[PDB]
Length: 99
Length: 52
Image (cartoon, chains in turn yellow, purple):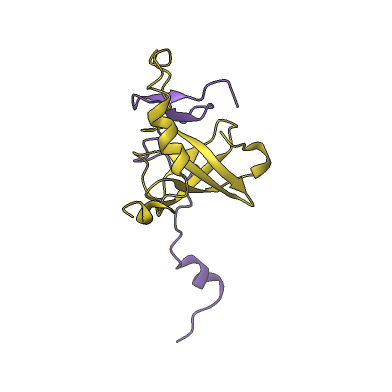
């Protein structure tokens, strides 16, 4: 009776698994050896395609800020969202991967 | 009242044309290096690491 309200869930944050995986891999006793995803001034690409890269993290990025990928191609933080950063790429997006 | 053409040339004022335009005046010219300077996790300005 009391579990009828939980039989299908409701949540925002389409990248739900990325926030859980930043909270469960430190619960492993072996991966507390600074096995930390950098999220303050760094970020990981979630999606990339047709000149738009969605980037997890980058919690200290400014709106309109020129960011740089590890490939060397630079981008611009255009959409600062609640759980990711939308980046328009200033080059060819074929050298950007997920992660 | 109209003098001439040749003495009309002698009553113009020549303006000094300056070679070496000198746009380095009041310019500070910060040193932009080759490698792309980025921010690491502690916030310091570091170059890009050698991985892609």
